[PDB]
Every structure is written in structure tokens, then in C-alpha cells.
Image: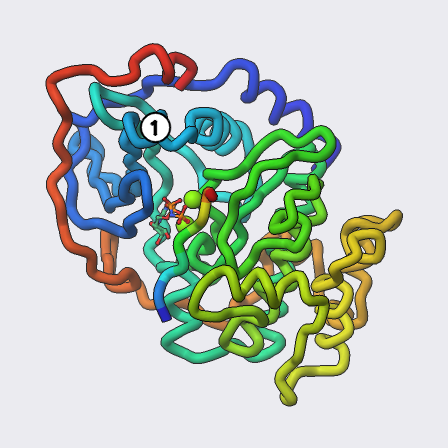
Amino acid sequence: EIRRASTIE
Amino acid sequence: FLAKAKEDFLKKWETPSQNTAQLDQFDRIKTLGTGSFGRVMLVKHKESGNHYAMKILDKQKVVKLKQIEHTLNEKRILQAVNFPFLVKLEFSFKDNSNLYMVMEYVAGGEMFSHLRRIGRFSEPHARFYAAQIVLTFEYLHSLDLIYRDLKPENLLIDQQGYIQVTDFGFAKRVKGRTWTLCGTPEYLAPEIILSKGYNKAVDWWALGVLIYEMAAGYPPFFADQPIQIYEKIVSGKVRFPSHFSSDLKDLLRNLLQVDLTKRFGNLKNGVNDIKNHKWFATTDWIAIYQRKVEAPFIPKFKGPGDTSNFDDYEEEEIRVSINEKCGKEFTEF
Ligand SMILES: Nc1ncnc2c1ncn2[C@@H]1O[C@H](COP(=O)(O)OP(=O)(O)NP(=O)(O)O)[C@@H](O)[C@H]1O
Ligand SMILES: [Mg+2]
Ligand SMILES: [Mg+2]
């Protein structure tokens, strides 16, 4: 649905 | 080709290119995508008229959020790789506030956009894209490189219908096992979630999540809060849609394997366990590498610099402080 942003923590 | 690709990577790795252009040479047309440390915008070179995609990163936020070595590896690795499915870096520089990476513009848009507007890809359509990912992962692993962010938002379709991989923000030379928690929650492998120390096997897990989301239209593990997604990733159970193939369910059961002593790509036979799976029986790997196969879907190109295949973002002007910040931290950029 929404562009999943990458995680860093 | 893999025999000669190793020397060329190491040649570009030790003698990288730096400061090849400046911000004054580029007109700024439209934003292509927004991340957490900056943005990517369509960019036109004033002297040559060529269009490019400029990835901008704020230097302060990178230093503040402990992202220095990650961004250093992004510029250096992408500058040093060469494969028909990887996006090519053309220019790179920096000013008082920002870092700049100028890549080749891919006007076809994300695979995430086309995946959502169509719903799902048929199995041969999804197989045509997975073959390119498998070939690229075989190349990157030959150079002992890791790519820890496989997701449709990082995969761009070009004018020939082929995949162009971008976003090397977590790429790293991994001679052994690494430890950094990073990626996209839907695509994280269980060993990353548990802080266990992972190798190249996480890329194959992410490939199984990608083949799932393409053939079904949705990821195998998703929930509201990311904590619950981790609960489903490490649980070991994965349920498949009913319209899936028996041949596809078998491959995904071997890619979405929690025990990495029995996961494909991590076994003794390496990438051959994947390329020689029954699901890929109809795949000419050489023809895919040479890009000699008619693509099943070809996006619409209304001309050069056309931004139709991208979403509309709130446009924000680029502004640099008159004080140089973190100059010593980004010397090697
Ligand atoms: N070379 C390119 N040509 C065309 N569009 C591009 C190009 N590079 C990036 N984009 C687009 O701009 C977006 C920026 O993505 P990305 O490079 O991943 O930034 P990011 O900060 O790493 N986002 P994230 O994946 O959460 O880390 C992409 O998702 C594409 O939609
Ligand atoms: Mg991205
Ligand atoms: Mg990224």
C-alpha cells in the first residue's frame, strides 16, 4: 500500500 | 565473464572516483523518491541535456545516526560494480551540507508501483524478474559483497522491461559474517532479527519474500507494528495462496527456510540449487544475462525526462548552509 522504508534500528 | 569481473571490481575499489561534477551543472526538475536521510530527484545536465537521478543525503543526519561507514560503502561499492542489472553511477560530489550521487535515470519506475497497480504478476512474469535477481546475486556474491535491502521499492524497470537494482545503502564487503541490524522489516531474515550473525544467506531469504510478493501481490509476513512482523518471520510457518504452483511452493519452502543449514543458496551447491530448481526449468539464464528475451511488460515512455511512472512528492528546494558541516568525516567520499 505504502512504500516501506528501510530500518536501521 | 565472472572470471574477469573480479579484477575490475578491485581496480575500481582501490582507485575510486570522487568529485566529478558540481551542483551548478544540474537543473532540478522533479523529485523521484524520498528516503530518511534525503531525497532522489530527476536532474538534467545543463551542458549536455542528459537526464539523471540525483540521490541527496544530509551529512549531519548521517553522522548523527551512525551512518558514515554505510554511506561510504554505498558510493564506493556502486562505483565499483558492473552488471547489466545494476544501476550505474555517473557523478558524485559534495558541498557544505549534502552528499550527491548522480545515477542513470530509469524512467520506467519502481516495480512496487506496477505491482500495486496491477495487483500481482503471473508466475512466468514473476519468474522473468527473479532470474535477473538470481544472476545479480550470483555476481555480487562472487565479489564477496552483500546486498541487504532487496524490495520492490529498490527495483526499477527500464525501457527494455528489465530490472535495474538501485539503493546500495546497506551494501558491504562481507568476508565472513556481519552483525548490523538493517534492511526492510518485511524482508528481514530471522538471523538478522535475533542478532545471531549472518552471511550472504540473507539475500536468498529476501529473494523468497520477493518472489512471494510478486506472485501473490502481498508479502508473506506483514502486520501493523513491525514487532508482530518479526514474530511471524521467526515462527517458521509460512502459508501460501491456493493459486500458487507446486513448483513455486517448493522453491519458496527452500528459500524461506529458517534453518540456514538447509536454505537454498547457503548449501554446498550454491546458486545451482536455485537455478536448477524445477520452477526455473523454462529459463534461459544466458539469454537473460545477455538481455535477449522479450520482456512481458514494458512501461510507457512519453519521452526523455518523463516522470509519469513515478509518484508525485511534495517538491522542496535544495538548500545548503553557508557553513561546512562534518568535513573531516567524509574525506574519502
Ligand atoms: N537511478 C534512479 N533512476 C530512477 N529512479 C530512481 C533512481 N534511484 C532511485 N530512484 C527512485 O528514488 C527512490 C529513492 O530510493 P533509495 O535509493 O532507496 O533511497 P533510500 O533513502 O535508500 N530509501 P530506502 O530504501 O528506505 O533506504 C527509489 O525508490 C526510486 O523510486
Ligand atoms: Mg529504497
Ligand atoms: Mg536505502
Helix, strand or loop at mark 1:
helix
> Which residue appears at 25% of the width and 40% of the height?
B50
Left or right: residue B276 compared with residue B21 = right
**Image quarter hosting the C terminus of chain B:** top left
Picture layout, residue B183 above or below residue B282: above
- Here the colouring is rainbow
Residue B181 position in % (x across, y down): 55, 42
Residue position for label 1: B64
Q: Residue at left 60%, top 64%?
A: B231
**Residue extending furthest toward the right:** B268
Can you say which quadrant of the picture contains the N terminus of chain B? top right
Q: Give B289 or B202, whichever is nearer the viewer.
A: B202
Question: Mark 1: few, some, or many residues within 10 Å (few <14, many ≥20)?
Answer: few
Q: Position of residue B292 (x, y in %)?
A: 59, 59
Tell me, yes or no, if residue B190 can be seen here. Answer: yes
Q: Indicate the position of residue A6 as horizontal and vertical percent values.
A: 44, 50
B77, B193: nearer the viewer: B193
- Residue at the extreme bottom of the image, as rendered: B242
**In the image, is residue B64 above or below residue B249?**
above
Q: Looking at numbered disc 1 in the image, what kind of residue is underneath it?
A: Lys
Residue sitting at x 70%, y 43%: B196
